[PDB]
Length: 137
Image 1 (spheres, one colour):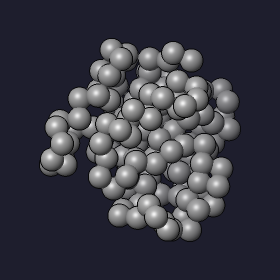
Image 2 (cartoon, rainbow, N blue to C red):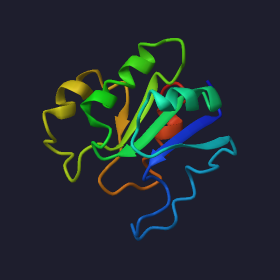
Image 3 (cartoon, rainbow, N blue to C red):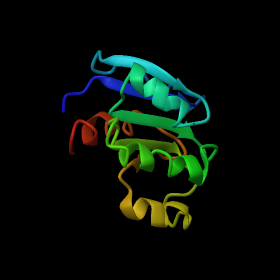
Image 4 (cartoon, one colour):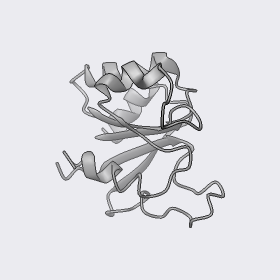
């Protein structure tokens, strides 16, 4: 519930000249276990890194570099049910497009067990990482 295993990949909370801050409210945040999963999103190799964290909040700020394969890879990590991380947060996802976004996650977000980060993340997004992923918002 009050899980302390947040793992972030690819881009993320660093601040890629967002012009806000550094985005130090996702790193430690609640002083929980801060671990990096790595680039790409490769859920299979990150299953071995799930032994490490065993992240409840599996986030990858992968701009479709994960692909719809590895997107459906984390659906299989949930549908694994062996390893937790039923709640994912799909950072980036596509590019600039929220209001009337693609048919990609129109159907994949139909289930949308995960949330999505805007094309210009803020910690308002990770306010929701730690919110909905504790259990509910």
